[PDB]
Image (cartoon, rainbow over all chains, first blue to last red):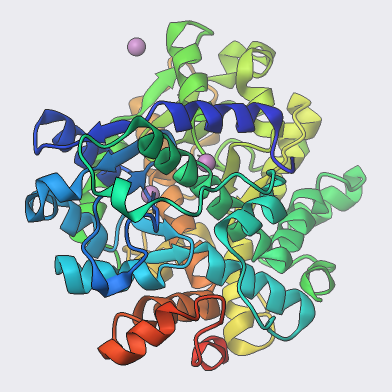
Length: 241
Length: 241
Ligand SMILES: [Gd]
Ligand SMILES: [Gd]
Ligand SMILES: [Gd]
């Protein structure tokens, strides 16, 4: 694990505590209001794996503290008109996704929802790789490959083959709901790690600031307190790469 | 304004709804628990403007939704031993600051708190500027300048010269509390804007993903659904500058 044991356990608990929503009722509106209080929500690709060829049977969204499964098959367009569309189309919250290409296609052509304002962790991995290796790799990384690489999770964490027929059977099984929740549970976290890893020069510049006065002897420190309109002398080399 | 009118009004409300804490009591523990639920908290530089030369009379911390003013002059080290130290020295939450140089100095030498894990918006404006202009500027930007530049706020938003004598008199005046709260109110939002503006290639790569399949005709779209281990054909061009 590259995440803490504490944080891992907290996410595992979140994975078990999902809320399933299959009517536009008070729990729906409470979910929509919680999603709208966040800077970032995560959206799973589960349910959109055929792009524009098929409607989504469900839509999995989370905050950093709570996972929601919306039963799109049963609520139909009502779930979108009652708040999900504005969430997905709006600037805020930003949507975290891992490879939103098919999600975007499915939402637009099957649900009339134009996804906008996304943090894509697959794109982030490509940016981190380019920053390090100068050129892009020839292939992209799966969500599970990223969860292993960035968080240290075991290789089998994501259930990648949900069965298309069971996903459309109702009542929706507990086994499928539990898989959907586990498959989204680490995505919020992944995004925070990838965002930091994208910004290595920035973070070196921060570390220069945090130390610049604090580590100096008194006379030096007092001289620097009078020169705060200036960049620290070691800053340019710090952020260099 | 470069922020929405709605968001502006939300932040001005937060600025008025601060909580003042001057004893290690139930409100204090409530605040520490709230701050520890967050990915990011902000920390104002107000109170630390002489670095190591003087103790902080107050410490102002905020979440995205709530401002807290802690009376360090009255609580003294109890406030740090009761939860503030671990917050400020821990990896999580990350602390947003604008120019943490003196804050870091004061916290360590006057309060035995080693600030760690910071997102510094002054550093972030430097990174943005270097990205755009190739080289670093010859001066740094104040918090007020960055608020105007990035959020569109008016020039006099920050009260940059708190009255030293009223800052150490108790009861702490409403005028000083109100200033302290106004001076931190916009810092969380500033950090979110600066974080996005640091990452322009990333965001163009994201827009490439959102459009790649969605904008294609059906034939192309379906071919692309069979080639998701590959990078979109225009992605390099998108992320190039
Ligand atoms: Gd988080
Ligand atoms: Gd309370
Ligand atoms: Gd925010």
